[PDB]
Amino acid sequence: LDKGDKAPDFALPGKTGVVKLSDKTGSVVYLDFWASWCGPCRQSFPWMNQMQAKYKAKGFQVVAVNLDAKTGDAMKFLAQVPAEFTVAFDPKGQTPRLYGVKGMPTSFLIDRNGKVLLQHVGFRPADKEALEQQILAALGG
Amino acid sequence: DKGDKAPDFALPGKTGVVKLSDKTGSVVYLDFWASWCGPCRQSFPWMNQMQAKYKAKGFQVVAVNLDAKTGDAMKFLAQVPAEFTVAFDPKGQTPRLYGVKGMPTSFLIDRNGKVLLQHVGFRPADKEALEQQILAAL
Amino acid sequence: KGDKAPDFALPGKTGVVKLSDKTGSVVYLDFWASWCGPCRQSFPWMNQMQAKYKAKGFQVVAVNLDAKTGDAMKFLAQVPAEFTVAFDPKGQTPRLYGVKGMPTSFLIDRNGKVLLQHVGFRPADKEALEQQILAAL
Amino acid sequence: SLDKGDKAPDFALPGKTGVVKLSDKTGSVVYLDFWASWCGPCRQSFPWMNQMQAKYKAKGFQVVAVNLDAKTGDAMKFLAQVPAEFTVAFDPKGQTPRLYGVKGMPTSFLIDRNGKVLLQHVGFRPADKEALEQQILAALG
């Protein structure tokens, strides 16, 4: 996918029911691909929680697609780590291929129209400032 | 899980394609590591000693990197020498296959390609234990 | 020209790279290396091309031939490459393709046969090459 | 994959004059090079190998350069413009480099008088010349 292309839609199981990218149309979406064994994911979660609470009123949603072989293991992770945003489970790892994911983690910022604005590989504290800047811009400043 | 068949894989290596199936007949210490994983700073020099010490008897270390950015992996290898086979799996295909739930994680595999153990983490106290497991496998 | 380009399975930056997967698309197979000066030019150019004709089915495959990948990474870390990259330190593919010089590029057609074998890279090549590319599209 | 101390695999390859066998060099310290006409660094390594050969031949030193060009004819073209005052062998099938665990082009080996590997050197750059000659000098006593 290139900036501007439409983010492929999907329907994945959630903790509550089903999670569909399409249902998030209208809101800037921070789509994240993570797994419980990925150390950087332990740092990105507190931050994603921060962004979600800070920008949810402006029509912003974090959608975190988990890629653990067993959702049970991800549930363990979530039992210890707060995730105050939508979480989807893709045990077969079907969506990351659709998105051309090439690293773990990898996140995508999708605009209110459902088009890709950016693809971010990996996560380190130094990524927070630039990423929030991108979020803020997509929300209509 | 001790006894299952270790999933096969084909990952890019530093000088070709790395396949677990190419190590059949040898004891294999399969390691999952990453630059962002601190314990790997200790595991590597140790894996270098083990690989050298038991190579003659049919022992082979295969260290699968899980860095999202290879640049970070190379940076790490530039500092921490790895005198053993290294493979790259940024997409996380193999850790998903092996059910990796923590880091680092290693698997000791017998000559018949079957799991002998799964070891999560790495601390000085693990070295003797693991080396005994290696010795036992040989 | 018209022969048929030999396939291969080389390690990539994020998986295995196989010329066979680029079927149906025009392929600009390029053999480069960090020690190859003309490559610092061919790259920015290949980026422009890949972007410009990718919509019409243009695919650039740059096979690196550095003996030390560290050297290749060092290069790619300075000279961004918006296209598929493969590494062949052992130099297996250049042997299959009879590479006689560097840099050397092979423009291939959707039928993966070979339309062109180009050696070297100088500013005066870009035009003709882009032309040969456009013609292939 | 050879280790220092391991016996260097023998071979019999065609040469310009006749056949070339590593075993005919037993007793001499050998600098075994794996090169090809398309490999840039080889244009720098050849003048240096010519220098080492002239400087140490009297001590029982020999450079053996196994060519890996697809067609020996192309190698012959290279040799027509680049002096090679040492033994040259041609391995168009590329059988020997695999036997030696060659992982880069070029790659060279220093072999002691007993036919055992002293070192494996990958690539070639002017910065390599000094350390390489020190190794050669040592092997020659």
Image (cartoon, coloured by chain):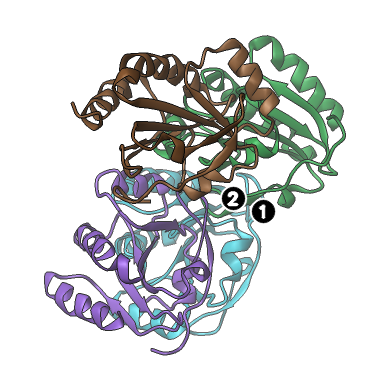
Chain colours: A brown, B green, C purple, D cyan
Tag 1 subunit: D
* Residue D100 image point, x, y percent: 60, 58
Compared to B126, does B4 lie above or below? below
Q: Is residue A84 left or right of residue B61?
A: left
Q: Dots 1 and 2: beta carbons under 8 Å?
A: yes
- Amino acid residing under circle 1: Lys
Camera-nearest residue between B79 and B3: B3
Per the model, the C-alpha gap separating discs 1 and 2 is 6 Å
Q: Which mark is residue D7?
A: 1
Instruction: Please give the chain letter of the residue carrying mark 2.
Output: D
Under circle 1, the secondary element is loop
Residue closer to the observer: D133 or D71:
D71
Decide if residue D43 is on the left or right side of residue C69: left
Rendered location of residue B119, percent (x, y): 72, 22
Kind of residue at badge 2: Val
B6 horizontally vs A69: left or right:
right
